[PDB]
Length: 48
Length: 174
Length: 174
Length: 174
Ligand SMILES: *[C@@H]1O[C@H](CO)[C@@H](O)[C@H](O)[C@H]1NC(C)=O
Ligand SMILES: *[C@@H]1O[C@H](CO)[C@@H](O)[C@H](O)[C@H]1NC(C)=O
Ligand SMILES: *[C@@H]1O[C@H](CO)[C@@H](O)[C@H](O)[C@H]1NC(C)=O
Image (tube, rainbow over all chains, first blue to last red; front, side, top):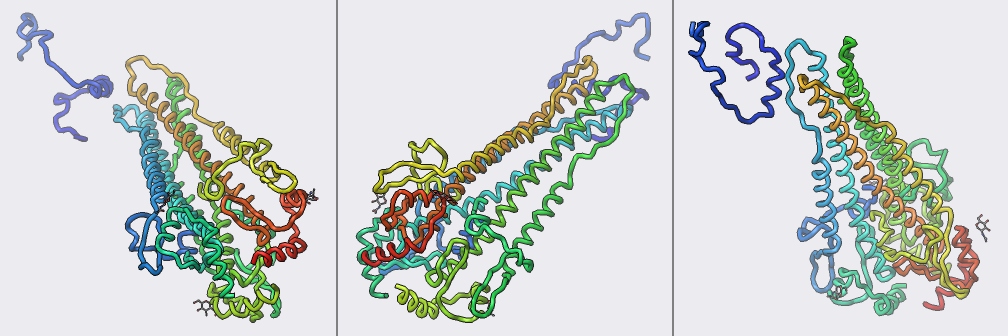
C-alpha cells in the first residue's frame, strides 16, 4: 500500500532503505536460514 | 479530397456494393446490377493492412516507465526522475497522435487515387465511344451484350471493331 | 505544385481578385470583371484555420525546463540533469520544425487541388460547348447574357438547351 | 502511384533514356530516337538534392551519449542514467526512421506529378491534332519535319497554322 500501517514498529530509520528496495525488484525468491542461532548467546541475554 | 474522386465527380456512394470497395454499375438491356473488379480492391486491402501493421511494428520500441523511490532527503533527484519519466511519455504520446493523424489523411487520399485512376482508365478505354455525363456515367453507342461490360471490367477493350458502329452512331446524331 | 493547378495550366495570378481566393473571370458582351464563389474559398478558410489551431492545440503539452542546483561535489548528477534538459528541448524543437515544414507543404498542395477541382467542374459542365485554350480559358458558343455566367458560378449548368445552339455553331465552323 | 503517371497510363519505362529522367520519344519520317527536356529533369534534380540535404541538415542536432559511472551503492541513479540514455536513442531512432519512410513516399509521388504534368501539357498543346492511344502515345495529323517535334519539346506549339491541315485531315477520315 501507499501508506503502510505496520512499518518499522520500533521507532527509527532503515539505512539505505531505498537501496534495498531496488534490489528486491530483481529478486524473485527469498529463504530464511539460521545464520546465528538463538540460545547460543550464553553470556549476553537475548530473550528479555 | 485532394484528387476529387470522392465527392467531386461522384458524390454518391453505392450502398448495394458490399462485395468489394471499387466496382462498376451496368445498366444495359440484359438487366442491371453491381459488379466488382478484384485488381483494384485487393491492392487497397494489402496497402491498408500493411499500413496498419506498420504503425504497430514501428511502435514496438517505446519508453517503459519503471518505479524508483527516494528517502525524503533527495528531492532534486526525485523531481529529476519525475520530470524525466512523464517527459518521455509526453514525447511518445505526441508521436503516436501525430502518426495516427497523418496516416488517417494518407488512407483517405490513397482511396481517392484508386477510384480516380479506376475512372481514368475507363474513360481512356471508352474514349469517343461513350459520353461523359458528369457523375462518372458513361453512355456508349454500340448495342453489344453484357459480355462487353465484362470486357470493360477485365480492362480488355479492343477499340477498332467498336469504332465503326460507334462512328455510324456519331454521324446519325449529327 | 504536384497537382499542377498553380503554374502549369494557369501560371498567372489575378491581382484584381481581392474578394476571395478562388473565382472566375468573365469577358462577355455585358462588360467584364472578376467574381468569386463562396463554396470553394470558405472550405479553404475553414480547413486552413483548423490546421493553424491544430498546431497550437497539439503543442499544448511540452517539456518545461525547471531549475535544479548542485553543490560542486555531485557533478555526474549535474551533467545528467544538464544533458536531460537540453536533450528534451532538442527533441521538441525538431518536432516543431518538422511539423511546420510538413504542414507548409500540405497547405500549398491543398490549395492546388481546390483550384484544380474548380477548373475540373467547369470543364465538366461546359464540355463540348466551350474550347480549352490552355491557360484555363473557356470560349463557349452560345450568345447568352451575363446570367449564364452566374449559372456557371452557382454550378447549375443545364446542358440540353444550350447544346442545340452550340451544335449549330459546331457545324458552321466545320 | 497516387497520380497514376507511373504505371497507369505509361506502364513501361525506357531503358534507352540515359540522358535524363523525363523525355519524349519521336517516331517520324526522319528516323526515330529518344530526346530529353532539361526544364523538367533539372527541377527534379534540384528538388531531390535539396531534400537529401534537408534530412542531413535537420538531423545536425541530436542527443549525444556520454559515459557516467557509479560506485555500486547508487544504483537508482545508474538505472536512471541508463534508462535516460537509451530512451533518448529510442526517440531519435524513431524520428530518423519515420522521416526516411515519409520522404521516400514524397520522392516517388513527386516524380509521379512531374511526368504526369509533362504528359498534361503535351496533350494540352496537341489537343485535337493528335489522338490519345492510352499508353502516352500521341498520333498527330500534319506531315511536318522533325523540327515540329522539337517545337513540342520547347513547349512552343503554335496552333492555328497546324489546325487547317489537321482539320482537312479530320474531314477525310470522317
Ligand atoms: C478477363 O480479362 C482477361 C485478361 O487477359 C482475359 O483473358 C479474359 O478472357 C477476360 N474475361 C472474359 C470473360 O473474357
Ligand atoms: C444559384 O444556384 C442555386 C442552386 O440551387 C440556384 O437556386 C440559384 O437560382 C442560382 N442563382 C441564380 C441567380 O440563378
Ligand atoms: C526552343 O524554345 C524557345 C522558347 O523561347 C525558342 O526561343 C527556340 O526557338 C526553340 N528552339 C527552336 C529550335 O526553335
